[PDB]
Image (cartoon, rainbow, N blue to C red):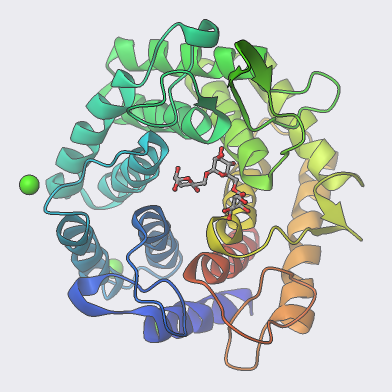
Length: 338
Ligand SMILES: OC[C@H]1O[C@H](OC[C@H]2O[C@H](OC[C@H]3O[C@H](O)[C@@H](O)[C@@H](O)[C@@H]3O)[C@@H](O)[C@@H](O)[C@@H]2O)[C@@H](O)[C@@H](O)[C@@H]1O
Ligand SMILES: [Ca+2]
Ligand SMILES: [Ca+2]
Ligand SMILES: [Ca+2]
């Protein structure tokens, strides 16, 4: 029972990482630092549990987390990293779609206004990484911005938001997507006076949000090109290459990188749920999530239920919250697909 596994991990995560004010600590050792974007993804994990169970017990924990983020972020929701605001805004819109709780919509509305301010024509378009890095346009600040815009379009049907989604996605595809594989390069910035793309950094979460944005744009327009884009990127995830070792999504370390795998699995799974996906691709994608979930469960989880950065080995020491969230996201995705 994969839902039973996910619920066990939800409980272990909440029990080990909950700190004051309804937020979640950086690790299970000596660090109580508040990580804004990690806590945003804990909200996503709590939403995963709510959708699977229908258990209203998740709702007060979600609300306490939303309000605790405001306090620990300095009595505000704005953050210097634009991608951080995008992650929280996405989770807030997800919550509003399921609960109609206007408090989440108001936060999302604020964060969308800030996200749109990061856009510029530097490097041809794209949302900046930070409010003060006008020249650094990163996949992690554009993939999520498109997803953000698409959720808002589903909710408010403002034509300007669909235009934003299309413009963000098409800049991302034209700039940071490898035309041969569909995988996503990390960023473009000025180095020694000229624009350079970091092609060495190919992370699971960047192709993850590209897949997620393409899937949502296909749903919002019906244009097959978006589905073709998503299938190509997801097929490269499955086939041997940069992001897998022995068919398992690879170790990307702890800290921020601990969260990368879970984000890819979330949006990969959403593509596997698209009704227009061909049967053979759906089977291949479902089998890939199962293989990863089985690997983590049997090889990578501690007996208490903590996941490490390598899904194929148990962590012997500190477990960052980000790393743990990727494990819970994997199990929730597996339970969703059964
Ligand atoms: O070794 C450096 C980092 O490499 C890997 O992270 C890749 C990303 O690094 C940057 O983003 C990191 C964090 O920056 C802010 O705090 C905020 O935006 C956070 O949300 C963000 O995660 C940036 O260059 C991104 O474009 C890269 O993709 C991981 O291994 C990290 O853990 C590691 O510290
Ligand atoms: Ca429970
Ligand atoms: Ca209920
Ligand atoms: Ca305030």
